[PDB]
Length: 309
Image 1 (cartoon, rainbow, N blue to C red):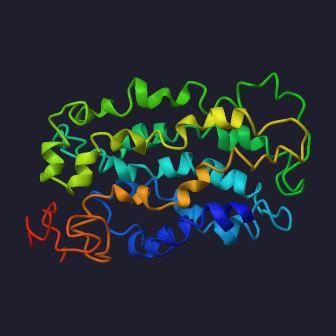
Image 2: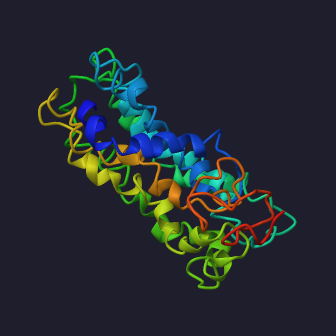
């Protein structure tokens, strides 16, 4: 964790470091184009601090150990950087989502969330089977009395290759191929229809040029980190010889905690990067500042046209 930060994420710090402040702020202005900062930004978000507070000082090392609760790298970030980021995700249903509308649906529910809603978020978070069964596999090996274990595996890391690894992917998170994201009806009218993002992101409905790019950035909103991670845990964060590996923090943890680079993360903001108001020092047109007085009169031109305000 030392080395990791000390060099490698002396790049999160200070680009992200300073510029977190410019951005995040109680998730600055929910709920137009700022999808990421509504969520994914909770897990990822938190990695940064995080940092000393829960993953350097006290959080896998030192003493130690700690955590408290189950690492507490493990049972926090290592699920929270799925489930709970993605369970917050309803505050993206109201975005990757009302890029257009598919208006109101019927007499109900045009209030898009609520039902779907759970038939959205209670899908994108549904690897919530780890919280349970993986999590039972930190209880024991109890991830505090043990320190992080050791031990009390053997039976049956072999025989329950079902619920552990590899299950958190299994084919479970084949969701964004098979029905998700399209299945919203309106998402059978975005990206896949060049009748969207293009015309309507050059200068319609939302925040501009970056909202063009989510013709393709789109799909990297929901198969980033969490989707492919089962194959990472599979080899390895289970057996070998407890103490040296697991805890194999070396390779398997390093990718998810590059999330501290809030730079290309944030880069594809949209409606509240340009037409931002507060913290008018982001990527845009005039660039890296303005012209962005503010208001909130739809999109942004390049620049402070169309329209103040």
